[PDB]
Image (cartoon, rainbow, N blue to C red):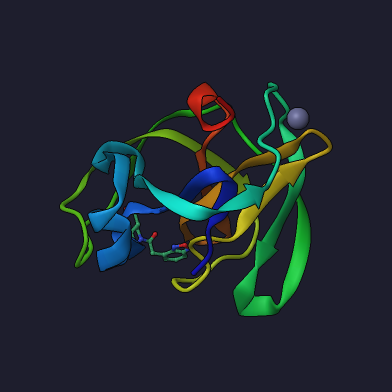
Length: 139
Ligand SMILES: NC(=O)[C@H]1CCCN(C(=O)Cc2cccc3nonc23)C1
Ligand SMILES: [Zn+2]
């Protein structure tokens, strides 16, 4: 579990979105596992606007933050689940690091701000859904 709160927005993994998220839907993309809903209270998360390939992510399954090197956002194959059929997930970044289902929603950050959230993982790898291209989250 986990979300990004920037201004009047809440960014969550689309497969973990609530009924309230869908009733206050702004934008969603199955191919990226993202859903953005509107909020009444103000959010203060700063979104990074950069091409950083190093950062720190929160791992709930370990109650620890870990430094990582991660790849550039790309289309990566992801296996089937109770949420999606087998497909290519776009805007996805992989890092060598620990993750387990339950870790989705953990924030990845660089010195510039929020880079994205945990969305996939397995076999010593962790995948992050990038949010840096969503320029409209700030305006
Ligand atoms: N974006 C998707 O299609 C997801 C949907 C939920 C299930 N997915 C996983 O990757 C499970 C998983 C296993 C093992 C470490 C994991 N860390 O985070 N998620 C992990 C795929
Ligand atoms: Zn950065």
